[PDB]
Image (cartoon, coloured by chain):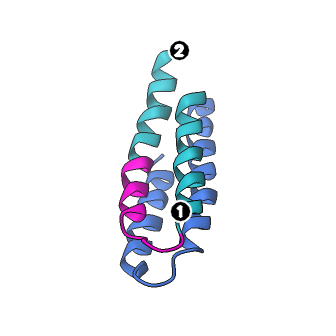
Chain colours: A cyan, B blue
């Protein structure tokens, strides 16, 4: 059911917002981290 | 169904691992960030 996927996406939407705050806080060695950090969450959202 | 919750937890388990890597990377102004970062993911896992 799409509700399950929506719930999953909703959870990740929340993770993305908090993760974004962390990413907006770290400004040094997070260029590589940002790629994996955003890529992974994006991959999870994209995959599901 | 518990499968939905398990899927949700599984997604957060994945977020926690990646988030942990970010937290293990940032070492400066993330004491406050860590509290919210871990507290939020923990809150989501705890709540669901």
Magenta region includes residue A25: yes
Q: Quadrant of the C terminus of chain A?
A: top right
Position of residue A47 relative to residue A2, above or below, is below
Q: Are marks 2 and 1 in contact (CB under 8 Å)?
A: no
Whether residue B45 is visible to the viewer of this picture, yes or no, is yes
CA neighbours of label 1 inside 10 A, class few (<14), some (14 to 19), many (20+): few
Q: Secondary structure at mark 1?
A: helix
Residue at image coords 45%, 41%: A11
Kindly identify which chain the residue marked by label 1 belongs to: A
The numbered dot on residue A31 is 1
Question: Of label 2 and label 1, which has the lower sequence position?
Answer: 2
Q: Chain of mark 2?
A: A
**What label does residue A1 carry, if any?**
2
Q: Quadrant of residue B9?
A: top right
Dominant secondary structure of the magenta stretch?
Answer: helix
Nearest to the observer: residue A18 or residue A1: A18
Residue B10 x %, y %: 63, 43
The residue range painted magenta reads A15-29
Residue A39 lies within the magenta run: no
């Amino acid at each position: 059911d799409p509700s399950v996927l929506g719930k999953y996406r909703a959870g990740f939407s929340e993770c993305m917002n908090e993760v974004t705050r962390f990413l907006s806080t770290c400004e040094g060695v997070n260029t590589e981290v940002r790629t994996r950090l955003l890529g992974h969450l994006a991959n999870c959202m994209t995959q599901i």
